[PDB]
View (tube, rainbow, N blue to C red):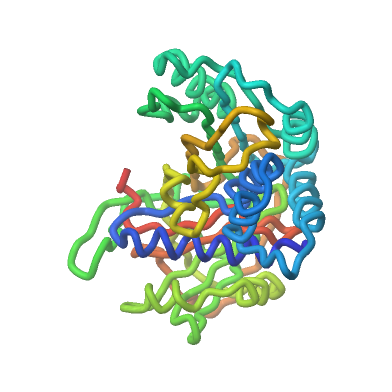
Length: 372
Ligand SMILES: [Cl-]
């Protein structure tokens, strides 16, 4: 793992826990890497308390880790993510939208693009309709039509908007068969069910029951170099599971590549998290950059500037296999013994971890696959 990976994992937990505290009856899905990288990039146009709040709010202890190490960490992570031959189906973008008429520092726009692969734009925020359409149409192009009408309301006074999007439709190394998917109960609570398409495969899985977490733990690899890890808590143990997750625990799971016989039920779902990062990151202690006090002098030298709007949109599809064009053919040997049936048919927590850095690309919880 990279040197900033542990801070990223702690950030993931802090933001997840915040979101879990905010509601227990909604699906959660967000990108820790995506949000952190966007605010690491923003921090380059900041100074002092404004700057320090962002990095401390991303779980860096600035009396401990040098700022340069933080940035080459995000850099290195943005290098493995943006491989030419990635194979990982990961569309991600950062849109900086600043009012026209501000004289922008060249080096900030130079740092943004040719270090953090973000996009900077000068727009007339005088007309909300033009500015909103400019913002949504950029996200439309960037996701290739997968995210539309993202921004619902822009303020009249908005001078600076950050939009952060991510769509992920993964291809399983060891995929499910479409023919075996059938509609089944998902237990949204102890007495209520909902119908979901349930994917099913008898095979050899990295799957075990962890008594410490009171959870079943499933790891499945994606094409590209990322791993989905699913935690299915015993009854009454969801909150325990949320409380007890650590990065060292996830690391231990990824280090074991043992497989056992199992009949797995995993729902086919599409989930999205839409987050107001001003609200949400404000709760983690990032307030100055969003206020009149903000020192954004690395973005514009003479004029007062604050971050008016910051939005995260995360979209995920889980299916049998996110592409219908193959080549790699294999054979798992199932022993004669009767396999456990393990069904992810009630609320569960997940992470997608990029393999080279051990970064948490995504974290989420499914409470109701039909909750949209
Ligand atoms: Cl796998």
